[PDB]
Image (spheres, grey):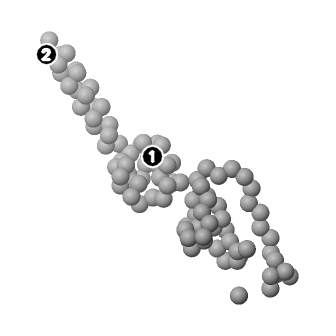
């Protein structure tokens, strides 16, 4: 019974911690990349994310 | 009519006086751009 709780919590923690990954973008923060790149390149950067 | 200096600004996603105050092109434009020197005809 403890393993079900542990596995569900771990999967959710991994899912949330996946928002810290760049995936090749200049930055992982959408607002940060949008605030300093013009649209036709910010589009490309956002698409990878 | 445009001048050769900054003549290349007529294109999607460009910056400058022309593309920001005079004539702006959308990001998803489809169609062709044509230019040619007109010294013999146009040269305040």
Q: Which residue is mark 1?
A: A46
- Quarter of the figure with residue A17: top left
Q: Position of residue B29 (x, y in %)?
A: 65, 52
Q: Secondary structure at mark 2?
A: helix
The picture places residue A9, in percent across and down from the top left corner, at 20, 25
Crowding at mark 2 (Cα within 10 Å: few <14, some 14-19, many 20+): few
> Is A4 or A49 nearer to us in this picture?
A49
Residue at mark 2: A2
Q: Residue furthest bottom?
A: B44
Residue A33 lies, with reference to residue A7, above or below; the image says below
Label disc, if present, on residue B1 of the rendered structure: none
| Residue located 14% across and 12% down the image | A1
Under tag 1, what secondary structure? helix
Q: Is residue A37 placed above or below A12 in the rendered structure? A: below
Task: Judge from the rendering whether residue B21 lies leftward or rightward of residue B35; answer left or right.
Answer: left
Reply above or below: B42 against A16.
below
Q: Are marks 1 and 2 on the same chain?
A: yes
Q: Nearer the viewer, residue B10 or A11?
A: B10
Mark 1 or 2: in front is 1
| Residue at x 74%, y 60% (from the top left corner) | B33
- For this rendering, which residue is in front, A23 or B42? B42
Return the residue found at the far right. Answer: B40
> Image quadrant of residue B40?
bottom right
């Amino acid at each position: 019974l403890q393993d079900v709780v542990n596995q569900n919590a771990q999967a959710l923690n991994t899912l949330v911690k996946q928002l810290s990954s760049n995936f090749g973008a200049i930055s992982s923060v959408l607002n940060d990349i949008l605030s300093r790149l013009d649209p036709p390149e910010a589009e490309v950067q956002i698409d990878r994310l | 009519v445009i001048r050769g200096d900054e003549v290349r600004q007529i294109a999607p996603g460009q910056t400058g006086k022309i593309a920001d105050y005079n004539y702006k092109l959308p990001d998803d434009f489809t169609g062709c751009v044509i230019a040619w020197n007109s010294n013999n005809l146009d040269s305040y």
